[PDB]
Amino acid sequence: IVDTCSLASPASVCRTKHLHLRCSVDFTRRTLTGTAALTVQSQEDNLRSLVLDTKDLTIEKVVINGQEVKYALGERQSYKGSPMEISLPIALSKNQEIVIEISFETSPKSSALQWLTPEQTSGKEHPYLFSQCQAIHCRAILPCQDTPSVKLTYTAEVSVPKELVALMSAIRDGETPDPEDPSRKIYKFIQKVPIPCYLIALVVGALESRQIGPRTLVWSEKEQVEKSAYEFSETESMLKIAEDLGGPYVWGQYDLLVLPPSFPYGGMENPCLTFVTPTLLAGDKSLSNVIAHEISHSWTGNLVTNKTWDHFWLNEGHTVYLERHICGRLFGEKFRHFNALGGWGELQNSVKTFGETHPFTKLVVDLTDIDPDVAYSSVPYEKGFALLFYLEQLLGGPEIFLGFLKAYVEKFSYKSITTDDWKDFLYSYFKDKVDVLNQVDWNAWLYSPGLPPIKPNYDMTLTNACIALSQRWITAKEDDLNSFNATDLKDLSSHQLNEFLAQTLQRAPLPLGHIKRMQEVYNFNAINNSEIRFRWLRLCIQSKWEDAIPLALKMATEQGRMKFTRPLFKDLAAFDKSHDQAVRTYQEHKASMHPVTAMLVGKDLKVD
Ligand SMILES: O=C(O)C1CCN(CCOc2ccc3[nH]ccc3c2)CC1
Ligand SMILES: [Yb+3]
Ligand SMILES: [Zn+2]
């Protein structure tokens, strides 16, 4: 089984066992410079060369056995970067290991990295750097077999200006002054658990920490520490539930890092150090499902890993399934059903947007010649979850299916697997229920586009009030608008308010007068909850409310979570009155945006 996103030698040829990274972070040049020493095991007899992924990397030299060796960089292959073939000085027998030390430098335009000026930070005095390797950006940091089919341990020494702090997806292993430069510090790191290289992460900035649990510190700039400690105070209780469901947490520490606003995702499950968007800081812990999600990846994703990106649903579907169980344990089974039903709504939205026959609406996708960043959507999350929730209901309930989940994590821990491996184990675990399993339309679920062939059963208790209010608004005529008022919202949680808006957004546009009334009576303009504000602004823009233009533009640009920034820009571009402003704002902000976000927004806008 071939990873069509990687140009490196496959796991069947050789396997990286370990990376020792020794580098220096240069904020003046916006480069990372150093050596990556790869311990590689031959899987073949008489192995004489091998190939590594690179992207925008400057290679100085490659050293084996203390001597320089021949290598060559192939022609760049778009988003895949350039393959690097290395000639081994002596042929290797099967299972023989050697160390290959590559001296390299990154480009300032590394798609893995965002370099922030002091003014793009909270403190305004120091610069800031962060990485994001998933799916295939590790190659834009260092030469590697950039495929999740290979797992390696790592150690790193990172030299940074002494007033700044380095963190990695690893256990902190001490700090010292840089022996070769008084103005610099070296931070050391150890990751003892084998990981796919997409989980390598690095932050450098003016970071402070606060403890919030027996194995959790929150890290951020000083201005955000207090708020973050409170927002994420459920972390330990969630880790406890996660361990009950998934087995031992094997990674030692579970720290959180709250990034600056340009961070492109809700979170990223970097082992030992989850990265999260500051757009989670609602002030009431209401967006903590994102933390439950990142915690869950400690089992589904980081222990059991997708062998190629075609099988990404394995990572995300199971993680959302565990995420919803954590939240269901904390807040009740009716709440789990409410979230599950909301997720089905998001799947409807994704399918409608792509088109019901689009290949990216397939559960298992074929990424040959497709940039994974372009293919990325809610489909693998929600169609994946829908499959598992359907299977749960078919096979006798949540207690039974959780038994399978834990056994699946156990079976495939430290490994990389395909959808077939998963299905084979499902059939093994439930061998006494194979007749029921054979009733599943596997070909439809796994390989067909569109909505799943069957929708699960959802408890409606919490959803009813949201649908009822949304329907009141949708069917209202002008002479009904007077009946609405602030008391409509009195018994709705923030989650229900969000769902009301999601329900209403699906029927957008509404009449402009309706939207004006909704602001008049509910004052959604005052809500800072990022999810609620996002849906409200989309509703306003799609319903042609000019007053909403500056609000939408401000939210699109003052944070950069792609979930929010991409649809806000797209809506603003689709609205005749804001179209020119949207394009102009993008052009102006482009240079200081995250490189992946810049790329996708440009594509969305048909710009450049
Ligand atoms: O799921 C999470 O925890 C979030 C969202 C997804 N994340 C980064 C997404 O990047 C990827 C990774 C893998 C992918 N396969 C296809 C598209 C694609 C995009 C990390 C944080
Ligand atoms: Yb009427
Ligand atoms: Zn995830």
Image (cartoon, grey):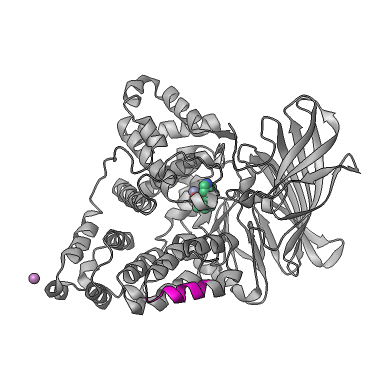
Residue 47, image x, y percentages? 78, 29
Question: Does the image show residue 310?
Answer: yes
User: What's the residue at 40%, 20% (across, down)?
Assistant: 431
Position above or below: 290 against 360? below
Q: Residue 485: image x %, image y %? A: 20, 73
Bounds of the magenta span? Answer: 577-586
Vertical placement of residue 106 versus 573, above or below: above
Residue 284 image-quadrant placement = bottom left
Q: Is residue 435 left or right of residue 552?
A: left
Q: Residue furthest right?
A: 67
- Image x and y of residue 326, in percent: 41, 47
Observer-nearest residue: 32 or 283?
Answer: 32
* Quadrant of the rendered image containing residue 475: bottom left
- Whether residue 170 is visible here, answered yes or no, is no
Instruction: Judge left or right: residue 183 versus residue 536.
Output: right
Q: At 64% across and 53% down in the image, what residue appears?
A: 201
> Is residue 579 inside the magenta stretch?
yes
Residue 561 higher or lower than 550, as above or below:
above
Report whether 162 appears left or right of 430. Answer: right
Magenta residues, dominant SS class: helix
**471 relative to 199, above or below:** below
Q: Quadrant of the N terminus?
A: top right
Q: Is residue 147 magenta?
A: no
